[PDB]
Image (tube, rainbow, N blue to C red; front, side, top):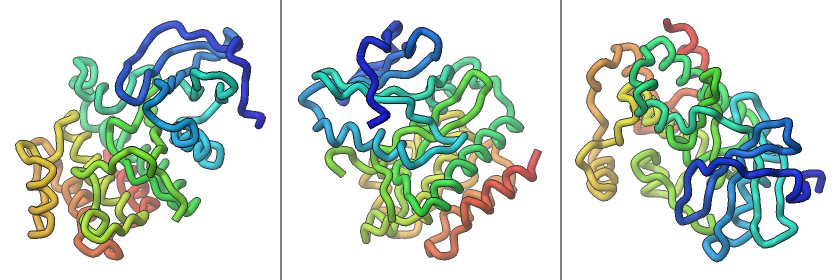
Length: 257
């Protein structure tokens, strides 16, 4: 489409992290604009499946969602070119020395920004299904943007749902809705307020989905305001229909300080 650009208009400068699925790089499109390049390591995924993320990003465009600039698909090493996020994932950032110094006011902000991006997704009648701090990216001005739309669908070829972030009715009955994203968001609040701690410390994925069938919820976590725990408990309601809208979460979070 007009999303294809020639490989030559992209220079890869610094490697940001590898893995099984591929690499992530900092680069430039035409020298001027600072970009992020996601590289597909060939053989791993299909080219259609790797591009499904970008394919979705063509439709989902908002300030609190990482934007797609272009793709390189013409030749073997496929690239996905997106907006550069200087501070990396929210998870990495919260765990860094700089991130550990960020107090509650900006944590609630972070949280309210993500609820804003989600409110767009739900208004667009979409679901993310993989909502967690490692899939949220932080810019230099400390703006939060939802990234990783690999599991996003309109309401899987080779990427698993994040068990410890997934709603009980989704695990047990395969019911993925915007309300299950609301659950995930509750767990994401837990990651923010604890500075990137794993959900359900010392529990395997299996312990968790067994415990959730017995109605377990993580207890009020240290250094978490009563009101903010009430937000989480609202996202973790057993009945999906009784969980709040993302438009509401963004509203109540913003009224905090």
